[PDB]
Image 1 (cartoon, rainbow, N blue to C red):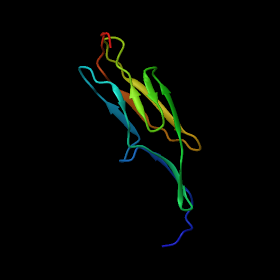
Image 2 (cartoon, helix red, strand yellow):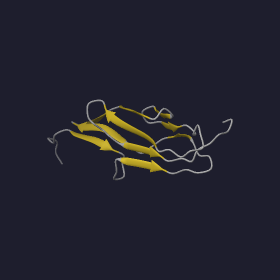
Image 3 (cartoon, rainbow, N blue to C red):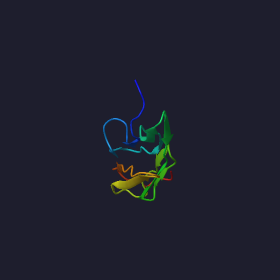
Length: 105
């Protein structure tokens, strides 16, 4: 075709949403990766953008990396975390509702 469109930022997961939730059982915690989008497309390029996060203590982000630690008492909480982008406002909502533990792990 041609070129001449404005910049477009990308600030979602990837499949049609901006919010994750998980409901593990027994014992499920560890480090995974997620289908998230964070860039601005313009010219004939995509500069990616980092994001930052926080909420509960036990939840860890390293760009395209994710971990959520296993629960410190037997209660069930909802762990809750936000995020935002460097040049933009990529907000997602992360929830983890895990049953709780008391074990030497």
